[PDB]
Length: 223
Length: 223
Image (cartoon, rainbow over all chains, first blue to last red; front, side, top):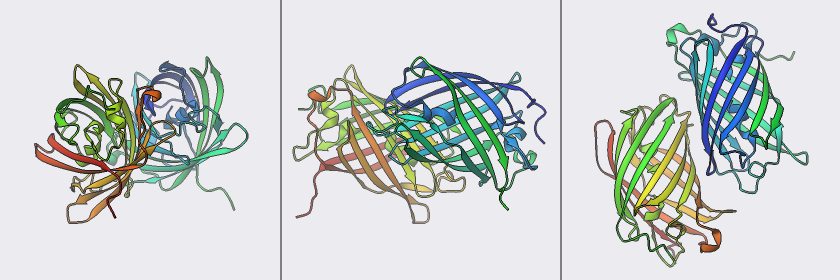
């Protein structure tokens, strides 16, 4: 039931705008991935408001759900949604008071996936590791997903590596909404997505960033 | 040491844009108030995305800190900030899972206060009173304000009255940031702002709302 419109190799283009604390910025990105293998790479440019006065890491999860390897016959909410596409909306709450919300539209245009993202980041502590750029990327994580009243609810927790060897914890809560009529969708049951979000390259005081994700959907895997 | 640029009667103009869940909208408003008496009225129009599929009440606090009567000699962070102006950034968390963040710029242009607001609301329950438009306005509230590492931190709790006679609780956490050099500012200590938010009139499924606020700053009122 995955859309035939999602091929083995797919390109993406993204536009992102928002504010973190009081700081306005815009990014664009281009990427390529293998939707059925759950892998993708994005090459990202900060085009307004750079270099950013906050850790780029807080933007990482806002740059792609079509590129999850849905194993074990798990119905794929995201690949099913095409050609109509889907949205997502999310809050990430950091233990030390910062919050980042994002709202995103995913469409498919002329064979290319198009992402449009709006970011609102608020109350990050002025002397904390995000605003002081003391962060070193994300540990691997697992999202749990299950049907919401409409759409799909996701929850995860993530750990941000800090200089000096410690961690900053956060929680993520998401709702994914399909633009495909509900009667044309086979909804999954409860399941997990295991993912690794890895930094490949950064240049020019983090105004150019390459990042990669691997994401695989499964049920529980312990006897 | 308030700015002489803030007179006894001031006008405001506002532009607001955002998304709640997946729903894009834009609002504009025109207003007037008495900054030193802590009273103001705004005439608000939904200009894109109307009628909104959520309760207007969730936008009420995003439509004005210059209009607080700062009593008891409390240094007035907002009135001192002109001509440069100030920004605010906020998360409101609802007990039933919705979150609304907002970021705001306050400027003074040709004697008129100009507000620019961006809204990101996420995860409002589909059958909850906000998305079902079963709300009846806000009870009176009190914000506590005190210096942050830079800026002014605010916290509040608010109760949204519901059709049927119950309440939906939320919490608000804000940072106000002055665009005036910190050496030219006298910071307050800890204080409270008591407020009431009311409507004068509304029409056409809340696509027109006239909102009024009275806000007075004080210290504890108990002997």
